[PDB]
Length: 49
Length: 49
Length: 49
Image 1 (cartoon, chains in turn cyan, orange, blue):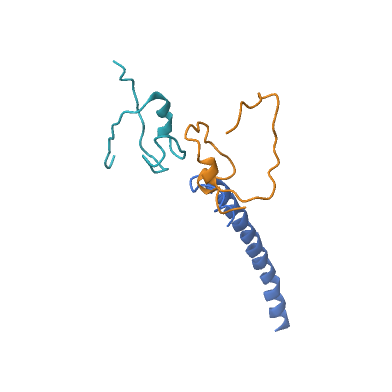
Image 2 (cartoon, chains in turn red, brown, cyan):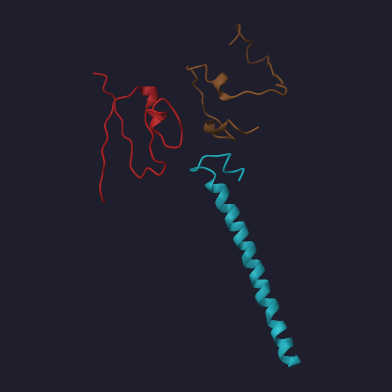
C-alpha cells in the first residue's frame, strides 16, 4: 500500500456500529466525522477485563 | 411531550394544518434513538415547505 | 435541482448517473439519426449538382 493510518479509541458497545460511514450517531455527530469513501477498515474488540 | 400515549393498535394519525414550524421544537429531546430517515436527509428538513 | 436539496452526496449518485446515461443515450440516438439523414441529403445535393 501507499500509507496506512491507525487510529485507536474507546467507545461503548452500542456505539460500535456508529463508526459506519454515511450515517449519524453519537460518534458520527459533531464529535467525529469521517470520509464516505473509507478504503480502510474498522476492527473492534472487547476490553471488559 | 404529553401524557401516556396509546399502544400501537390505536393510531393518533394527526392532520397538521397550515402553520410555521422548524426543527427547534423537535430538537427538545436528547434521548432520540431512531434518528434514521428516508426521502430527505435529516440535515435539511429546514427551509423547504 | 430538487434532488440536490433532497439527498446526501454519497447516496443519489445512483439516481444521478442513470439519468446521465439515459440522456447521453438519447444524444447518441439523435446524432446517429442525424448522420443517417445527412447521407441522403448529401447524395441528393450531389445529384442536384
